[PDB]
View 1: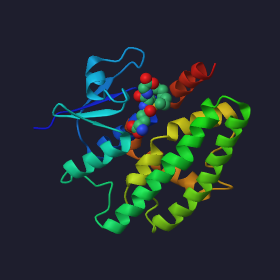
View 2: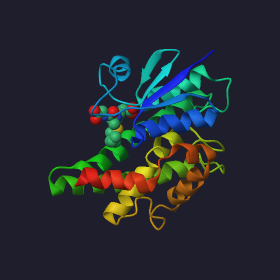
View 3: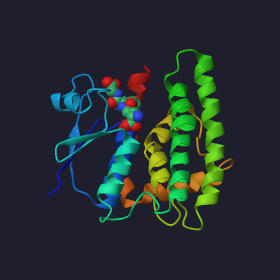
View 4: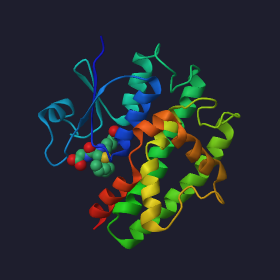
Length: 221
Ligand SMILES: CCCCCCSC[C@H](NC(=O)CC[C@H]([NH3+])C(=O)O)C(=O)NCC(=O)O
């Protein structure tokens, strides 16, 4: 039939996205843990170009990059469970637009906030991350259509893209003292966070914040 194996390291948000996607469709797969200081031959041969996770392996064939994997699953397993992407080409473009926004205007500056070298750098990342969240709120306002997700009535691509970093966001709040989806500024997003984490898929896939936090504090130190 179809064997699926996910190569990942549990703290990675990029892995978390793929786990959400698999869980959303109810797809069974083997979850394989990779040590990034001692990568397996299967990892090194499946993603020789970046040697990064996640990597989904389907019947022995690798697919890399979290958002690409998500669409690969959407297309191959269309007849199984809900789709992350809409049917309509316009709607699909818009969703891809916001995924890109998330990656470039949110996740990247957030990374800089966290692993920035100079304090100014940490501070600019932070600043940018916050401005991005205010823009994402307007996107949710326009995409919910009363269902509450970036995908409308069901979880979509954008929801997963963002959803994958939610454990890290909570960890960030604990380290910094700052609330990323502060309800007073971004009430729609604060409520979206609560709706998302309550999904069964999210419960199965998002990493534990306590462990995540210990892991983070050791890397910061
Ligand atoms: C586990 C700590 C979490 C830190 C965030 C980095 S996630 C791990 C990192 N992978 C990500 O960079 C992949 C990004 C890729 N754009 C995706 O979307 O799938 C990796 O495998 N890096 C390989 C390596 O570090 O050797």
